[PDB]
Amino acid sequence: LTPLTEKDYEGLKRVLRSLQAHKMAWPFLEPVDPNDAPDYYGVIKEPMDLATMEERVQRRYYEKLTEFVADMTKIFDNCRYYNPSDSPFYQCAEVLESFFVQKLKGFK
Ligand SMILES: CCCNc1cc(-c2ccc3c(ccn3CCCN(C)C)c2)nc(S(C)(=O)=O)n1
Image (cartoon, rainbow, N blue to C red; front, side, top):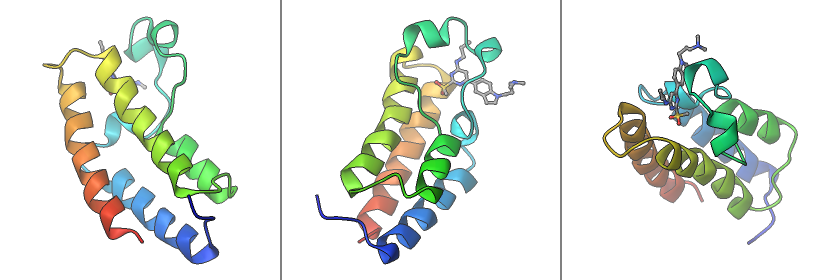
């Protein structure tokens, strides 16, 4: 979709910080440590996390909003694939994705 402006990027920074501050974002703040998730990097071919997204935002990696949404969705999709639906980690993805949607709709 449409090219991101500098003003758009300030809004993306705001959304990212909101996610990083959320009480249920802690499993997603940094790349998964293999010691905390057996076989994680054998299961998940395209890992993603909020620190990697922050680095990409600061580097102006994103050209369009779809690319930012895609990386954010990877975080949630990876979590729900790796973990069972009754896992607390799965629930964190449920809560934080709903929050992301609220914030993304606000973003314009
Ligand atoms: C047994 C299957 C568990 N599945 C998991 C586990 C984790 C996870 C666990 C601990 C964690 C973080 C983040 C910090 N800590 C604590 C510190 C740990 N060390 C010292 C760095 C994530 N994240 C997911 S995830 C990303 O939601 O898919 N799934």
